[PDB]
Length: 57
Length: 77
Length: 77
Image (cartoon, rainbow over all chains, first blue to last red; front, top):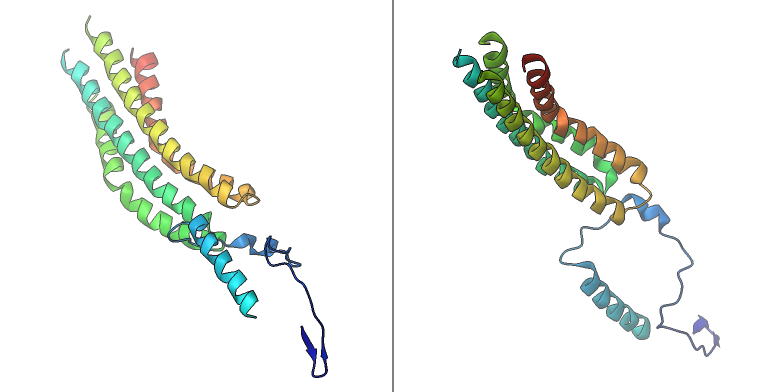
């Protein structure tokens, strides 16, 4: 982890199973996406792409 | 006499079909009004407006048939 | 004579068609209502309200059909 321009610390972090979000999207109550084509096959791709960014990061 | 048999029979078949039309015709509409609201309910007052706008058109012919049925049953006896 | 027999027949036709209409209309509307709650439970307060508002219009005409069927069966027959 790059923390300061003279301080870097080795970290082991968990990617999957997905770590727990600090925030709550209960406030997203009031709307829902018009999932085209269908939500499950889409969540699969979303999760695969997400681990990739975090690794790349 | 024989007339007052069929004068009622007709009034039934006209007002029965006029029901099947008016009810189902609105239900098919109302469903699409709900599934839209059940996604983003913030538009409920908007969509409800459009709902009535179109529903008035649905009851164009059914209420005409109901009026003719009432005329046949009561005025024509 | 023959009058009461076909008066009952007419009321029967009227109420059978009215039942078809009311049943299928409220069925198609309730199907979408039961979908909306699942997508967004917690607004059930609200989808049920709108569902009743629509059900009243769905049943407006079948109620007249039943009213006049009874009017025939037990005032004219």
